[PDB]
Image (tube, rainbow, N blue to C red):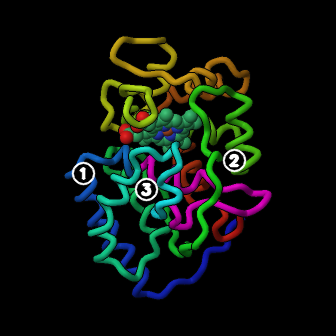
């Protein structure tokens, strides 16, 4: 249900050049997981009932970075600022969502479609919309379904973004990677989840809640067996997330 805005040719050219610069930078700095977390926290504050929050540039504001869920993202904002400055015509909103798409691409994931045109909005959303790692399947539906308006399939696919990166005890308090290859975007998050706890590796209570719910569990089994299907459903889910409240809700 989307109607994308028209942007000038100069805007379009800047998008294309920024994507190339972002690839090289993100690869060099080894920070893909962090950029993916930044885009996800930027978008995941959207609430469809009030049409507030979502991917509109606000995560750079000191008021939003202080949200406790956002521990560590000040690093990500700071890292990107000198590059953003080379592209003054782009909104921060677009730039951060593009960083997220590129993070998936450069770690070997699917090519998520990207449409430009998000505007930077002045008011950050209220704290507390991002999900709690200690809660379960009901909470996940409250947040992704009721607030953001995504489907159950989207919830499972997007959880698979834990295939890259790690928790840090100084940020959330949890510690460690979910997979043994945390810079490679693949389906191993789902394979580690099935085979159970392994020393070295992390499972949140919210990751485990996927294994026990009647709807989530078949999707976990599908994605553990078929990386192609995971990549397809992931690209679809990431696109929707990156576009919440944009070009029609
Ligand atoms: C499903 C509900 C989710 C919960 C409860 C959750 C929670 C967390 C927590 C607690 C961390 C550790 C932060 C730290 O200590 O540094 C984390 C990291 C991360 N999250 Fe999630 N998350 C969820 C969904 C998502 C989604 C939808 C995405 C993107 C598609 C995502 C991407 C990531 C990435 C890439 C990291 C690693 C960050 C790094 O390596 O610095 N997560 N998440």
Judge whether 157 appears above or below 101 on screen.
above
> In this rendering, would 10 be left or right of 156?
left
Query: How many labels were placed on the picture?
Result: 3
46 is within the stretch colored magenta: yes
- Crowd band around label 3 with a 10 angstrom C-alpha radius: few (<14), some (14–19), many (20+): many
Where disc 2 sits, the SS reads loop
Instruction: Rate crowding at label 1 as few (under 14), some (14 to 19) or many (20 or more) other CA atoms within 10 Å.
Output: some
Answer with mark 2 or mark 3, whichever residue precedes in sequence. 3
Of pointers 1 and 2, the one earlier in the residue sequence? 1
The residue tagged with tag 3: helix, strand or loop?
helix
Relative to 29, say whether 212 is above or below. Answer: above
Identify the residue under disc 2: 150
Closer to us: 134 or 27: 134
Is ligand 1 closer than 8 angstroms to the Cβ of mark 2? no
Query: Marks 2 and 3, how far apart in space?
Result: 18 Å
SS state under label 1: helix
What's the CA distance linking mark 3 and mark 1?
Answer: 13 Å
Residue 178's image quarter?
top left
Examine the rendering and report whether any part of residue 115 can be seen. Answer: yes
The residue stretch that appears in magenta: 36-59
Position of residue 136 in the picture relative to residue 75 (left or right): right
- The residue shown at (37%, 59%) is 77
Is residue 177 found inside the magenta-colored segment of the image?
A: no
Q: Residues within 10 Å of mark 2 (few under 14, many from 20)?
A: some
Can you give x and y, in whole percent of width and height, for residue 58 in the image?
53, 64
Q: Nearer the viewer, residue 46 or 28?
A: 46
- Mark 1 residue's CB less than 8 Å from ligand 1: no
């Amino acid at each position: 249900g989307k109607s994308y805005p028209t942007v000038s040719a100069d805007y379009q050219k800047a998008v294309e050049k920024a994507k190339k610069k972002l690839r090289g930078f993100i690869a060099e700095k080894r920070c893909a997981p962090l950029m993916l977390r930044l885009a996800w926290h930027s978008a995941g504050t959207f609430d469809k009932g009030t049409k507030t929050g979502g991917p509109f540039g606000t995560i750079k504001h000191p008021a939003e970075l202080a949200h406790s869920a956002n521990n560590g993202l000040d690093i990500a904002v700071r890292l990107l600022e000198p590059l953003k400055a080379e592209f003054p015509i782009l909104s921060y909103a677009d730039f951060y969502q593009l960083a997220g798409v590129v993070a998936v691409e450069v770690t070997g994931g699917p090519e998520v479609p990207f449409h430009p045109g998000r505007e930077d909005k002045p008011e950050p959303p209220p704290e507390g919309r991002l999900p709690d790692a200690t809660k379960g399947s009901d909470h996940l539906r409250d947040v992704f379904g009721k607030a953001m308006g995504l489907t159950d399939q989207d919830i499972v696919a997007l959880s698979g973004g834990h295939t890259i990166g790690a928790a840090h005890k100084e940020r959330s308090g949890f510690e460690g990677p979910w997979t043994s290859n945390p810079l490679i975007f693949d389906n191993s998050y789902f394979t580690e989840l099935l085979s159970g706890e392994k020393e070295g590796l992390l499972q949140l209570p919210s990751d485990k809640a996927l294994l026990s719910d009647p709807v989530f569990r078949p999707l976990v089994d599908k994605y553990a067996a078929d990386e192609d299907a995971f990549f397809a459903d992931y690209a679809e889910a990431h696109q929707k997330l990156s576009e919440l409240g944009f070009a029609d809700a």
